[PDB]
Image (cartoon, grey):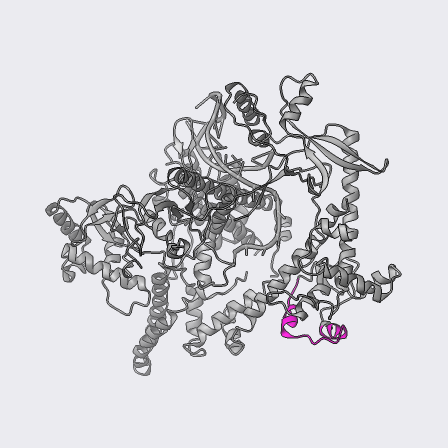
RNA sequence: GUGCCCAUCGUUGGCACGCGUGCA
């Protein structure tokens, strides 16, 4: 209803007058050097609190007295700091000495919380409070009364007030907000951290610690965290059932036939178990992350030592323990200041704005208006100890285009264009008035010999509720991220009722950014690179590089062979049909594998990485597509360089500084590429948000307010999803997209963001699933018989296998395969046979009989999901048996179902 | 003002965006 948000334009300061610039710099340095004084002083006041002083409202959600008090006078400050004097050993008795308090679990687990002893350490804040009292020559009773009074006005402890009220009751304000900002933020973060840990520490079994260490022996059999997704929590039971069945088939072969042939028996037993676990991970890997075969075979090798239901407990115990032991506490560190400036209660100072800029340009020999901004900032000069309002220059061209241009009429190539383009507006008479208002909270920070002013501003929303329309999007890396907008109560072709209202499918399509080019119109979100029509030299250089390397060893069958200059994937990656970005991704994966094997000779693997990233004309850094597999290219590049460092020095662990010292250029390259990927993921977030909000505006001007149906992880205390799908979702910070989209929702009037978990959003048939009854129809892959392969027939016939389908997806694909047989009359006896050419011929005959020409068969890695209505807007009415379904696009139907998931609640009939 | 896209880097190339606490 009332949610204001900030917006800054990251302006740039210019040195215009050395004397005044240095005066402002001296004032800023004065305030910056005075800020640590207030930081230490407020630490001193905070540490002085004692029990019986919080005996007021006591309005905390679940924070006990012990935790609040300990955290408020126990903190982890940098090692090189005055408050030193305590060690992490005697913490319990130290707390006991203060007010005779018993350290309970609530406070103990805070105490029993690890920190980074390399740079931080615990500080007393109580003997330091006594030191402050002594240095102030004030009685302990007086200081205690003063701090109690301050806490009464919420001026110390948890959730302090703003510097305005503080200083009013207690130039000082701005340096104060750069001092107690950490004292206010880190305290709350730590208290919530301890709450979460206690809520996730007691829940740990505490009885399987023996089995936990037993399984942890796997690592001692770089270190990474173990999680339940490494086993397939609910399916390893069936895996061991099958392995037990095999063992019974091996007990007879072991007790009997003990001659010189049981060596082959044990070899085939090992092969059978390894291949069974591999098939187990692959089949479950089609819906989740494939468990590491190495871990599974290791644990099976210790099957006897662990019971059937003890492996699950051990792995979950390890997950909980190793996420608890890597989640650290928040150290209250010296905050760097920023010194915001505002026109309401901060240090008085103002951007002048356009009408006044025109006034001051007319009084001088300025043509009509200058390309820079002038800000009047109140600098308190020290030499002349007084405040003067001095004018300084900002150069934010974007700001000029946005709000800093008047309505007269209604290396520098790029930048100059923006002003000239904006200059043309002065003579085209198009730009509307901006209604300055002068409500900008300009921020001025001093790092070195420069400044980074921003000109922040506050924008209100007044969010609406009557969402006449809804919108959803996929935000996945499968392929073709997409969106779909659905109306609520329309009356037309689509009057499809869900429970009590006709949700009409308005539109649905892939969301791709438009980036016009001299001769084409590419899409950053899905370009996938060029089709290698002109990029022959780049791939040819890659071929020349990889021609001189013999081969590598795989792990599918524990053996591989080569003679000389054997290839790995060129025959299936050097095709002009393949996209450039995918080619680079595959090449980077191949190099990652090569270094994984060829580790000793890493000295020769630096020029190539440079070429793919810096030196190559079509380098990864230069040319890339802001495509879902594009982030895959950068992730594989990061992993490639990390593994290159880890396999060049092949043993204490090697840190970032070791990488610096070993090779300076490579480490700088990894940092540059990480920055590239960080700002590029920011770019994808903002661009997808911009398109979604623009299409939301389209709907708003068409019909009305539109929701977006995003995905949330925290702030709901549900977390019904496991860490498995949580990680499978949060990749490439998908939430960030949603996050960005809600931040922009804070300004684009009429929009509104609501997030819904990713559950029940995989194969649901839109508008019929959970409308009358659960449907959960499967996906397929429309295609002609002329381009089938072994995989398609293998997959469809595998769907026909009748067993205990633990995963509902397998059962639903079984039902889909039965429906496919009914539609085609495949004669399962003959359909489940070999010679896929026979199946293709039968499909061709069926298509010749029917009027249709392209066949339609179920599959997993396939698009063209079947819907019962017109969704894709290009769907054809294909009859399955007698159902006259619509062959829409799988991605669009996924966009449809990920939307409206909880519309029955997000859009109640209130 | 930072950035993103490009066989070629401009046709006056196209386009986007909040800077700073914890998010995998």
- For the residue pair A524 and A8, the one nearer the viewer reads as A8
What is the x, y in percent for residue A412? Answer: 58, 25
Asked where in the image residue A4 lies, by quadrant, the reply is: top right
What is the x, y in percent for residue A218? Answer: 49, 69
Answer left or right for A30 relative to A162: right
- For the residue pair A467 and A37, the one nearer the viewer reads as A467
Q: Which residues are magenta?
A: A92-115
Residue sticking out furthest to the right: A137
Instruction: Residue at 42% x, 63% y: name it.
Output: A291
Q: From this view, report whether residue A105 is shown above or below residue A734.
A: below
Q: Is residue A99 magenta?
A: yes
Instruction: Residue at 73% x, 27% y: name it.
Output: A16
What is the x, y in percent for residue A98? Answer: 76, 72
Asked where in the image residue A540 lies, by quadrant, the reply is: top left
Q: Is residue A82 visible?
A: yes
Q: From this view, report whether residue A657 is shown above or below residue A398.
A: below
Q: Is residue A263 visible?
A: no
Count of numbered tags: 0
What is the x, y in percent for residue A607? Answer: 53, 41
Q: Is residue A280 magenta?
A: no
Answer left or right for A218 relative to A803: right
Asked where in the image residue A240 lies, by quadrant, the reply is: bottom left
């Amino acid at each position: 209803n009332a949610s204001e948000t900030r917006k800054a334009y990251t302006t740039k300061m210019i040195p215009r007058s050395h004397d005044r610039m240095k005066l402002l710099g001296n004032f800023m340095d004065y305030l910056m050097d005075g800020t640590p004084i207030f930081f230490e002083l407020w630490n001193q006041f905070g540490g002085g609190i004692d029990r019986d002083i919080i005996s007021g409202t006591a309005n905390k959600d679940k924070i006990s007295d012990d935790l609040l008090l300990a955290v408020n006078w126990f903190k982890v400050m940098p090692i090189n700091s005055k408050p030193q004097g305590v060690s992490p050993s005697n913490l319990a008795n130290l707390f006991q000495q203060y007010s005779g308090s018993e350290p309970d679990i609530q406070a103990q687990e805070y105490f029993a919380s690890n920190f980074d002893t390399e740079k931080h350490q615990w500080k007393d804040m109580r003997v330091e409070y006594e030191r402050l009292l002594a240095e102030l020559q004030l009685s302990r009773s007086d200081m205690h009364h003063d701090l109690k009074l301050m806490y009464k006005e919420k001026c110390i402890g948890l959730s302090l007030s703003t510097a305005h009220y503080i200083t009013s009751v207690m130039s000082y304000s701005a340096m104060l907000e750069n001092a107690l900002s950490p004292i206010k933020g880190m305290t709350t973060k730590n208290c919530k951290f301890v709450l979460k840990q206690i809520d996730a520490k007691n829940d740990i079994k505490y009885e399987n610690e023996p089995f936990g260490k037993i399984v942890e022996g796997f690592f001692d059999s770089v270190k990474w965290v173990l999680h339940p997704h490494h086993i397939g929590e609910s399916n390893i039971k069936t895996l061991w059932e099958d392995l037990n069945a095999i063992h019974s088939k091996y007990e007879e072969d072991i007790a009997s036939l003990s001659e010189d042939k049981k060596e082959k028996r044990i070899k085939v037993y090992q092969g059978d178990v390894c291949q069974t676990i591999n098939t187990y991970c692959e089949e479950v890997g089609k819906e989740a992350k494939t468990p590491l075969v190495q871990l599974l075979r290791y644990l099976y090798s210790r099957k006897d030592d662990i019971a059937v239901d003890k492996i699950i407990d051990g792995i979950t115990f390890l997950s909980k323990k190793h996420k608890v032991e890597k989640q650290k506490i928040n150290p209250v560190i010296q905050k760097y200041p920023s010194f915001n400036f505002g026109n309401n209660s901060k240090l008085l100072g103002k951007i002048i704005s356009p009408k006044d800029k025109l006034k001051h340009n007319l009084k001088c020999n300025r043509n009509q208006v200058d390309n820079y901004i002038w800000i009047e900032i109140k600098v308190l000069n020290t030499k002349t100890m007084r405040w003067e309002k001095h004018h300084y220059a900002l150069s934010s061209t974007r700001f000029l285009e946005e709000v800093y241009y008047p309505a007269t009429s209604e290396g520098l190539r790029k930048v100059k264009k923006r002003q000239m383009r904006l200059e043309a507006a002065r003579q085209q008479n198009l730009l509307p008035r901006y209604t300055w208002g002068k409500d900008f909270n300009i921020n001025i920070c001093k790092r070195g010999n420069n400044f980074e002013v921003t000109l922040a501003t506050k924008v209100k929303k007044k969010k609406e509720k009557n969402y006449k329309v809804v919108l959803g999007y996929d935000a996945n890396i499968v392929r073709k991220n997409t969106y779909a907008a659905i109306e609520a109560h329309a009356n037309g072709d689509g009057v499809i009722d869900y429970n009590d209202l006709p949700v009409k499918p308005i539109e649905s399509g892939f969301v791709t950014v438009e980036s016009q080019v001299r001769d084409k119109s590419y899409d950053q979100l899905s370009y996938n690179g060029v089709k290698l029509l002109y990029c022959k030299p780049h791939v040819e250089s890659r071929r020349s590089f990889l021609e001189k390397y013999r081969n590598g060893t795989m792990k599918d069958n524990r053996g591989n062979n080569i003679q000389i200059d054997f290839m790995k994937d060129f025959e299936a990656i050097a095709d002009d049909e393949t996209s450039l970005y995918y080619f680079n991704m595959k090449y980077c994966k191949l190099l990652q594998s090569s270094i994984r094997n060829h580790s000793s000779q890493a000295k020769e693997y630096r020029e190539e990485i440079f070429e793919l990233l810096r030196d190559g004309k079509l380098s990864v850094l230069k040319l890339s597509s802001l495509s879902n597999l594009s982030f895959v290219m950068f992730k594989v590049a990061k992993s490639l360089i990390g593994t290159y460092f880890g396999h060049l020095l092949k043993a204490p662990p090697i840190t970032d500084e070791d990488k610096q010292k070993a090779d300076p250029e490579m480490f700088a390259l990894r940092l540059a590429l990480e920055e590239k990927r960080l700002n590029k993921v920011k770019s994808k977030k903002e661009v997808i948000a911009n398109k979604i909000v623009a299409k939301a505006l389209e709907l708003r001007d068409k019909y009305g307010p539109v929701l977006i149906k995003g995905e949330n992880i925290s702030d709901t205390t549900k977390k019904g999803k496991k860490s498995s799908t949580n990680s499978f979702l949060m990749d490439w910070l998908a939430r960030g997209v949603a996050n960005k989209v809600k931040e922009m929702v804070m300004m684009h009037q009429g929009l509104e963001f609501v997030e819904v978990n990713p559950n029940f959003t995989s194969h649901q048939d839109p508008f019929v699933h959970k409308n009358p009854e659960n449907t959960f129809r499967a996906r397929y892959s429309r295609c002609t018989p002329s381009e089938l392969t072994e995989k398609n027939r293998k997959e469809i016939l595998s769907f026909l296998s009748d067993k205990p389908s633990k995963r509902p997806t397998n059962a639903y694909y079984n039902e889909g395969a039965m429906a496919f047989l009914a539609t085609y009359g495949l004669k399962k006896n003959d359909v489940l046979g070999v010679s896929l050419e026979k199946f293709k011929q039968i499909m061709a005959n069926i298509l010749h009989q029917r009027s249709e020409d392209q066949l339609l068969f179920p599959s997993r890695g396939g698009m063209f999901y079947l819907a019962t209505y017109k969704l894709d807007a290009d769907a054809t009415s294909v009859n399955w048996n007698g159902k006259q379904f619509w062959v829409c696009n799988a991605d669009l139907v996924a966009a449809y179902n990920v939307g409206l998931v909880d519309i029955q609640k997000d859009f109640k009939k209130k």
